[PDB]
Length: 46
Image (tube, rainbow, N blue to C red; front, top):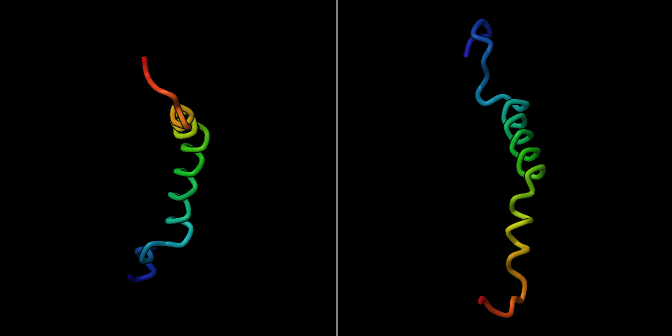
């Protein structure tokens, strides 16, 4: 990977960046938290 190319095997900040995006979107939506509410020692269904 010559310097001229300007690309390294999976850059640190690049993998980090992907992690950042996924974290922010999932937590903001909180879709998981809402779904969990449905379950919680429920009695039954009509």
